[PDB]
Amino acid sequence: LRSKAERQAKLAQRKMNRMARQGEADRHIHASMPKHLFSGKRTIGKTDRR
Amino acid sequence: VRYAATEIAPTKSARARGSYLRVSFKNTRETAQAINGWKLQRALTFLQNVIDKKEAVPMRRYAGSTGRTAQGKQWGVSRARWPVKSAQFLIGLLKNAEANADAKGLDTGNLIIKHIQVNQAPKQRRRTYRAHGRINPYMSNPCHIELILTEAEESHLSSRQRGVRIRRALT
RNA sequence: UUAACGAGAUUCCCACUGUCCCUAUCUACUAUCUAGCGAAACCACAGCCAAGGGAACGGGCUUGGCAAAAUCAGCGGGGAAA
RNA sequence: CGUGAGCCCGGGUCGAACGGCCUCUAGUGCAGAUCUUGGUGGUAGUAGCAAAUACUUCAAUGAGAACUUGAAGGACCGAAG
RNA sequence: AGAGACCGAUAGCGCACAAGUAGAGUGAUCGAAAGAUGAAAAGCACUUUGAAAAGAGGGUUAAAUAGCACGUGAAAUUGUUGAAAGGGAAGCGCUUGUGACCAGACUUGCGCCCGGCGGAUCAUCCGGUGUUCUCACCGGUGCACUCCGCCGGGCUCAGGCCA
């Protein structure tokens, strides 16, 4: 029963290991399409980045 | 478990398998195509020579902007490399298939690599940071490998044609 | 025709020198080759030219020149690329 | 088989429901919307992994040791470290 | 509390799930993704190869072509095997050819003339019944030159594809 228990614990980690999370506390959702990179236009005056 | 080559019966053949292996799929494909159809001991010696950089694997399909070497002349190419990690994974799988063949009682020294196939596994999804606060994928492309070792081994004529053949047979 | 002061703008002189005549050489880190790891931008389909293709435009059409696998380092004419 | 949108059958996979006809009904037919969401390529084993002087020998551990540890060396910070 | 010509997990409420959660923002606020092994865990004993993950045998199950990546398992895209093409694009239309792979059609039917079998649901008459009111069925009668099937021949006709 113990061996079955750690086997279940190890099989519970497969999706987060494929997502390459550092443990089960790694639940950060990053900005894949940030607004500052995907909106607005660049003029001759002040720009938002160099 | 189902292998790709279903025509090979398991009575006088051995097989080995590896899944979700974090080794480069392109390098592994080139190494597998290098050792395809070979004797087992010859394949093991070649893979050890690839690890020792004494013999090379030709890069044919996944070869874009790679270096050139004198060791591709054995294969008739110029682009060849030494993918030691793919060689190590394939050596482990080949030794497993050898052990399976010895368990079955087959003659190890007469075995050939009849089937070997590398597929793409689900990708390992890391992230990398770029300039201007951007994040891009930084994935690993792992592979499934499977291999199988095998012992080395006048009807409806016209009446005119019938008469012509009869006359030619008599004459 | 205002002294001092100024990372303000301008002309000249001496000194000085690879700015130049006119380029050469050396060192480090790259680029390069290998092991490991490994993106993105962009992408109708694709990519050799010449003349003609009324609407001053042809890469695909017409007529020619031609035309031989698979590749590596470079390059910045054209296509792409702000 | 039908000009056609489509319809029907055979073979394989599969496991719990479904169809013809006449009426009734509508959130009823996609290639485009720099469409939405999700997934996947070529590019491509490519660009790159080059600021902060620097690493080496033996032994041990271990399946495996440049980036573990002990010793032996060589260096750096140089008291606004 | 009861219902529906409603939706069937990108739909229906944002939420069928430890959802106003996880996460983000100083804050006011913003706000998801995410259902399905199997009837039953029976969730793989044991042996063997590996440092291990796993593999191979061998097992459970109706099925592992259902292995806690789990029903079915499409396309894009990828690997192996088999076939083919390629002198600066391929793809497409008309028509042959080669190779590979196939759907049909056909296999005999009908009608006479003989011979051999096996039976009397041959024509007429009688009675009953039903009907379309003149046509049938049922029971008796037939005594085998009459009817009905079978089996051998012979003959005529019609039969598939290309000429």
Image: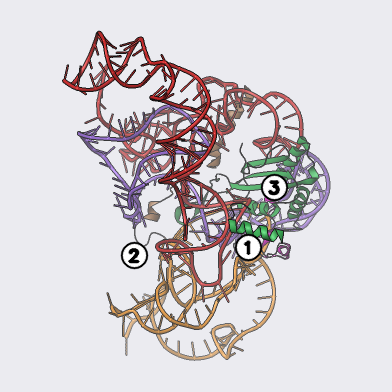
Chain colours: A brown, B green, C orange, D purple, E red
Q: Nearer the viewer, residue C41 or B26?
A: B26
* Residue neighbourhood size for the residue with mark 3, other residues' Cα within 10 Å, grouped as few (<14), some (14–19), many (≥20): many
| Residue C53 image position (x, y, % from top left) | 33, 79
| Distance from Cα at disc 2 to Cα at disc 1 | 42 Å
Q: Are marks 2 and 3 on the same chain?
A: no
| Residue C32 image position (x, y, % from top left) | 64, 66
Which quadrant of the structure image shows residue B122? top right
Which quadrant of the structure image shows residue B80? bottom right
Which quadrant of the structure image shows residue A46? bottom left
| Residue D12 image position (x, y, % from top left) | 53, 38
Inspect the image, locate mark 3, and give the three-letter code of the amino acid beneath it: Lys
The circle on residue B83 is: none
Inspect the image, locate mark 2, and give the three-letter code of the amino acid beneath it: Thr
Residue at the image position 38 percent from the left and 55 percent from the top: A38
The circle on residue A43 is: 2
* Residue neighbourhood size for the residue with mark 1, other residues' Cα within 10 Å, grouped as few (<14), some (14–19), many (≥20): few
**Relative to E140, does residue E48 appear above or below in the rendering?**
below
Residue marked by disc 1:
B66
| Distance from Cα at disc 2 to Cα at disc 3 | 64 Å
Inspect the image, locate mark 1, and give the three-letter code of the amino acid beneath it: Thr
Residue at the image position 76 percent from the left and 35 percent from the top: B104
Q: In this picture, which residue range is highlighted in magenta?
A: B57-86
Residue marked by disc 3:
B114
Answer yes or no: is residue B122 visible. yes
